[PDB]
Length: 188
Length: 188
Image (cartoon, rainbow over all chains, first blue to last red; front, side, top):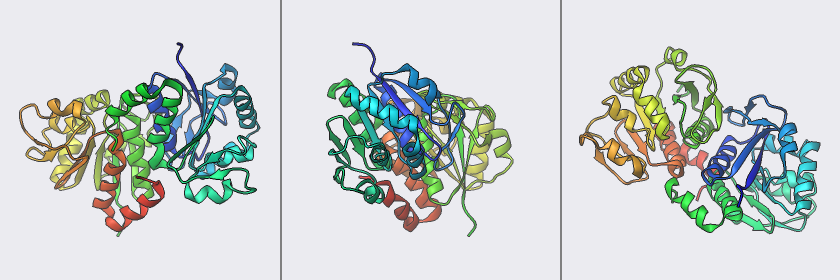
């Protein structure tokens, strides 16, 4: 096999923990991860002011597809920026069409709603984002810490980030690798 | 009470999750956090290549003390850099003298050993850093996910970062605030 590839879309206001945990854990899994800045290549100021420098602009990373998984971190403001981006809409639709994995956490899943992605899927979100996600009843809600309905994988919050990340790893590289990567993390 | 202040020392090779989780959670707790770059004010390349821009250089942040807590993230190479820094040695000694809290996670506590900080304390580390930390028997080892012996607070790894951060919050702002901050994180 070749190394699986992941696209993590980073926007201003993104929840930094929900961005870094998946990127870190996936790289620990041997996955080639690209942190793409929605607004460009400049540093991104996250929800709790942690400043992260993306690997490239989404505009450029978008031209290096396809990715085995597109990851949408949470954070209310970050998710809203994702929801309003035409570039994100296109990337997600193409990924869905390719039958590729789409993973979103916390408020991140509300971007799927905005772009009419995976309607009919069972999904979860941060408790405070449920109403927004369920507007129209286009999805069926779940309270599972991590929910995976086919190629739509969602999670609830910062505290579920490791489970979310390991779920992505399992989907891309298998249960054995996920387990190997998990042990050194010292998770409960 | 004025807001408590935290100094997080960020060095190349630092474990990004162990840096961001404590910074994020502490800021959620109303703590004024300063991410200080060991080598200066330039972006720092972490262990899994996540690039973080510090709020200021350690040189400058050092002059804005004192801090209610000095935080040492893990990551073998990051910890090594902290252990070799004369600036870190002075900061830690002052903090210990001031009877101020010192928190280190994963391999981070081996920097306490390097600077002869808190000898005699019960501590924990990432399992793989135990031998290094115990060289000379200057500390008593613990397998608790979070260990707090007086003003020396330690933790084991990425998966214990939330517990580690919430323990810092509890020590500085109390149990009520720690509980309030914890709820929205959706922790197990």
